[PDB]
Amino acid sequence: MELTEDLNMELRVFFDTNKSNIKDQYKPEIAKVAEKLSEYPNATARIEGHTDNTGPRKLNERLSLARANSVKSALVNEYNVDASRLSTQGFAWDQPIADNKTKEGRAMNRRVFATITGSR
Amino acid sequence: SHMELTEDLNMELRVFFDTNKSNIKDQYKPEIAKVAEKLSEYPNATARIEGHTDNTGPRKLNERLSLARANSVKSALVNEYNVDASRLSTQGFAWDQPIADNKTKEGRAMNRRVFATITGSR
Ligand SMILES: N[C@H](CCC[C@H](N)C(=O)O)C(=O)O
Ligand SMILES: N[C@H](CCC[C@H](N)C(=O)O)C(=O)O
């Protein structure tokens, strides 16, 4: 008898204009991610940050990455997760998921999407 | 909800039988127990149980025996571990799907089997 369990998770964190801090409402989901990273010790996370299309290019490139790093930082510093298991990358505004022509649209683009994959 | 979480279970069970028998030999109890445990941990998982025979004896005896073997594995899960019967399918294939040489005792022993695949997510 042989068996495997595969873990697949997606975490979505949203940010306010110019901010890269993790809102308190997202703490429970980050805690769950940490829990599963312990349950599946070989799991890794691909954290990708984004920004809306407003402002200078240099600002958003740094801001998108800062947002991804904030998520990684929470896992590393608050949950004892090894940093090497978490990759971070910023895409500025090059990958929107909503329309930047609207208030709510831009709100959706200011985000960090993290994909966690593992097996045991 | 700002998060999606999925765990996929894949499990393969193998049970072998003595000639003309469909009972579960005690040596397979641990495996069956492990399957039962995962079926509880993954309440929506289902199992595909398939029974077989070696090629000796009348065709109808083997059609019935192959199915009886599959049903014996299902019965263990259902009655000893209270698994919902509807989550488990059973089917017999007589001697139609050999995995070994019917010309040897060892090969025929390998053909008298039940293979079950358990899949599902939580
Ligand atoms: N419009 C903002 C700068 C751009 C922030 C935006 N690109 C983001 O992703 O937060 C400001 O008026 O200072
Ligand atoms: N010795 C008996 C029963 C054979 C059952 C066998 N085909 C199996 O899969 O257990 C016969 O040859 O008629």
Image: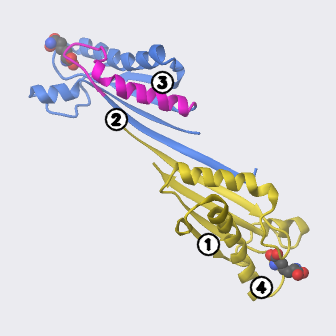
Chain colours: A yellow, B blue
| Side of B25 where A52 appears, left or right | right
**Labels 1 and 2 share a subunit:** yes
**Point 46% across, 29% down: residue:** B47
Q: Earlier in the sequence, mark 2 or mark 4?
A: 2
**Labels 2 and 4 share a subunit:** yes
Instruction: Look at mark 1 in the image and give the residue it sits on.
Output: A88
Q: Is residue A6 above or below residue B47?
A: below
The chain carrying label 3 is B
Circle on res. B88: 3
- Disc 3 versus disc 1: distance between alpha carbons? 43 Å
Q: Earlier in the sequence, mark 1 or mark 2?
A: 2
Instruction: Look at mark 2 in the image and give the residue it sits on.
Output: A1
**Labels 2 and 3 share a subunit:** no
Q: Secondary structure at mark 3?
A: strand
- Disc 4 versus disc 3: distance between alpha carbons? 57 Å
Where ligand 1 lies, by image quadrant?
bottom right
Residue type (three-letter) at the residue carrying disc 3? Leu
Cβ atoms under marks 3 and 1 closer than 8 Å? no
Instruction: Decide if ligand 2 comes within 8 Å of the CB at mark 2.
Output: no
Give the residues drawn in magenta, as a range.
B15-43
Q: Is residue B36 above or below residue A63?
A: above
Instruction: Decide if ligand 2 comes within 8 Å of the CB at mark 3.
Output: no
The chain carrying label 2 is A
Q: Position of residue A75 (x, y in %)?
A: 64, 62
**Point 51% across, 54% down: residue:** A118
Q: Residues within 10 Å of mark 1 (few under 14, many from 20)?
A: many
Task: Tell me, yes or no, whether the highlighted magenta stretch contains residue A117.
Answer: no
Mark 2 or mark 3: which is in front? 2
Residue type (three-letter) at the residue carrying disc 2? Met
